[PDB]
Image 1 (cartoon, rainbow, N blue to C red):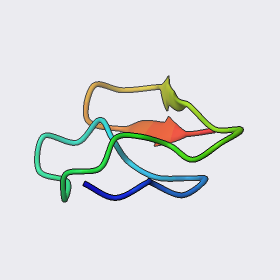
Image 2 (cartoon, rainbow, N blue to C red):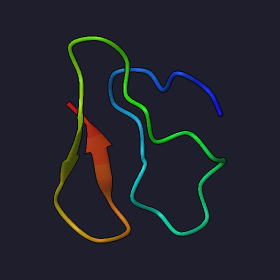
Image 3 (cartoon, rainbow, N blue to C red):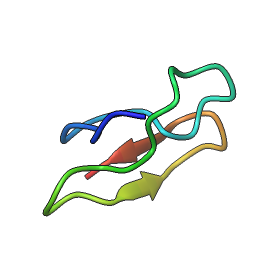
Length: 38
């Protein structure tokens, strides 16, 4: 699993593995399927 960039979908039950947002960013929730690195 990648070290996921700033602005990066962890949420989506479909996405290519990586949830771990890079230093400064954590995966901030909006929807279940749209949770994004911010």
